[PDB]
Structures are given as structure tokens and as C-alpha cells.
Image (cartoon, rainbow, N blue to C red; front, side, top):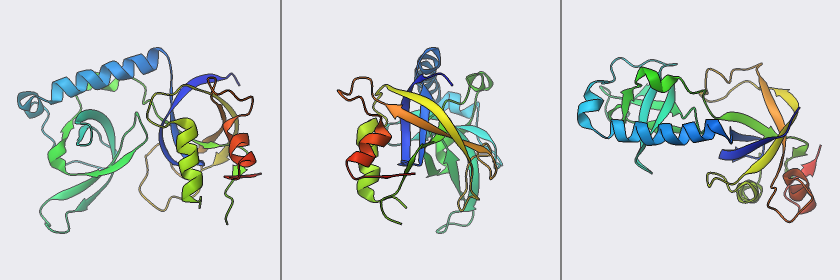
Length: 213
């Protein structure tokens, strides 16, 4: 397959992270985040889209109070508030970035229909040809991978899909697009501005943060 320019947008570990494609799609995503954020920042517009009787699988708009921006999100679970049985806590998967967060319904709206047009931008991947140094990944390995990818800071990488692995049985709530048996792409990654001929897997192995195979 062909190499592709990507950003790493979220990281759980070197064998669970998310990438976005750079190009017209990433420009459209940035434009959409701006437009959704401007639109839903108005109480009047939010009232046009009040959330009622939400359901698992629903695609919604949600504000992440971190950056105060509005994002497309998939409801992956709904549970009662523990303090308060008459309200729910909503498990959201942020379809364009890869993050998952538990969010109050107060911070969610229905998604205006035209915001559905853009392809969901995040693809879950694993780093091919590596495994953990200790038989889970050490926090230091996760940190090194976050550093090399500069996750969430718009660092261009070159990715290539070189293998696939069957998704394991999930132990937590995940996207409807990420069920057991579906193919998880295994990628090579390298930083074209890196000063190195080695890809990120080989950097992690040669520097003691991962093992081969």
C-alpha cells in the first residue's frame, strides 16, 4: 500500500492509537471544528438541537470542557449518575480524534445534519512489529511513543499499512466500528523531519522501549 501523511491524534499505547489523514480532509476537519464550536456556543442554537432520550450508537455534538470546543461524538455507553439516579453519564467516543470521555448530558446536543457529511476522521491503529518490554506497556514506553509522535500537536508523520490484526474481544465500551473480529491496521510510522533513517518502531526497539516481534 501507499505511504500517507498523517497526524497521530490520540494515544492509549503503541498498540492502540488513532491517526488522521493530512490533506483536504484535515483542512475540512479544522473548518468543521471551528464552525461547530461557533454554532453550538449559542444557547439559541443549542435549543434547536436539545438532546432527548439518547441511545448507544447515536452521533451527537459534545463540548469537551478542556478546550471548550465542540466535537462529533458517538455514544458508546449510558449509565446512571451514581450520586443521582435521575440523570445519566454518557460515554462518548470522539469520532474525529479517537479520545473517549464520560460526559454529562448537559454538555451534549443533537448533531446538525450537514455536520455528518465529512468522513469520521480518526482511524485506530497499532504500531507494527513491536511488543512490550515487560510481559501492558510500561508508562515510559507510552510516554516515549507520545513524544515521538507528538500526539495532538499537528506533527506530520508518514504512515504505511503493512499488516492487520483481528480485534480482540473488548473489555470496555468501544465504537460500533470497532467490534471483535474487525481488522485493526498495523502501521509503520516515521517522522520526515526527524534527522533519522529509522522509523518509530525501530527507534523504540533500539532505545529499549519495545521488543521486536
